[PDB]
Length: 474
Ligand SMILES: O=c1ccn([C@@H]2O[C@H](COP(=O)(O)OP(=O)(O)O)[C@@H](O)[C@H]2O)c(=O)[nH]1
Ligand SMILES: N#C[C@@H](O)c1ccc(O)cc1
Image 1: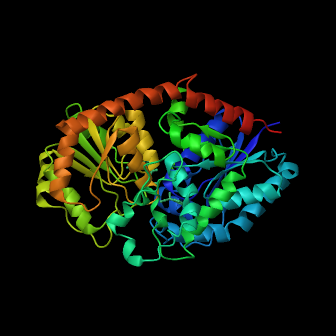
Image 2: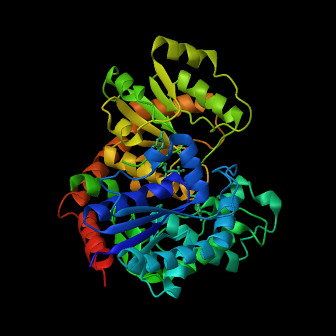
Image 3: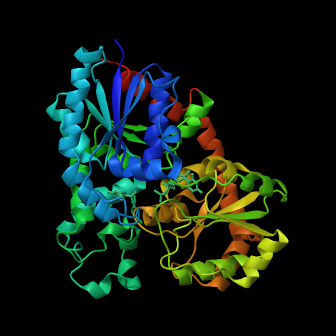
């Protein structure tokens, strides 16, 4: 019999990426895979890159099925409207997914298809676990961000119990002294402050979607057969040991993409700029500041201008990925100082890049990052120190660990100002600060390589997951 694994990501590129990594590995190991897209995600991908590039090749088409489910969303809903996405998916996708499972079962008789043997749902996509359990199909969940991020979400309930969520005083939502308050009761992260919790807790709404959905997700994941985390156990050991008490067995597989590399489908709405790596080839080793904020976050036009002026005055060449819709509001021209540096060849601004390859390029010496987890995993594998500007979600949690525990990063002020940006970049490029963070980044690069190579801790967890949980085919 052939195992048949159905995988269901949340519609964001940072969620699709790790589940697609796993789906391709399972297909390589001989499994049948059904990858489930929401119609929102599928139609947006089609209009950006065309059906041929989004769907599987003909060589893999036999055992790699793409299925699409309804979600009731307009394609106009932007990626930064996380609450709108989350609320529609949890309300609209369960019955479409239940129907999909039924049809996959009918295809056993109808076309000799393999019965479904496991569902791997993103933790967010609680309907996938609900439908699998109803149908008596094993399900395992994949949390796509950091362990420390999960630990913060897990403690949303405790915030509610302590009267901290919802915020009873709206004036405290952005009060920096209040947000600095230590939360000494979080196991595994004694240094958590209120601001270091994933940012969706900062709400006055007692029916807030993201708080509600978080609680649903934690309860769902606690009932799963296992939890997959795309992190390095050695990096997040104290956090993972604290999470162990609240979840089924946890498999730390990170960086999954590097485990796979040790040993045909576009998942992005943006086209990776091919000039990047050639431009970096022309720059000295370690000389370039690489700036990128991932696939969902947006910033203000004022923040964008201060980043631009800071980059122009920081003393280093720079590669800035400025996502086409990253700035809120109408298009504003970049400052002349930056535009002149681009004209001189000292800087380069592109809409999207091949991020893992850029971070591994010898010309890059620093990553200015929003602290999205996949981006941090790519920085960790590459050995790049991080200058952090967290935006939303668990980016704040990740930044707290980058600064206080992992040791491979430093933080910018949330209020962007060109002079402080230039000063901190300079410190990271030539100061004792950067020497320390870069040295620690080198240590984590070695640790990641050891974990991902055959026999390493993450490699061993991937083998156990792939074999004993997913290819069993009972
Ligand atoms: O120029 C870019 C920037 C990002 N990414 C990819 O987009 C995802 C960003 O995920 P992350 O978890 O860092 O952040 P999010 O987008 O969820 O904020 C990762 O797979 C990156 O490799 C990319 O392909 N090109
Ligand atoms: N930010 C962000 C997204 O990655 C996200 C989606 C759903 C969640 O429940 C939490 C976070």
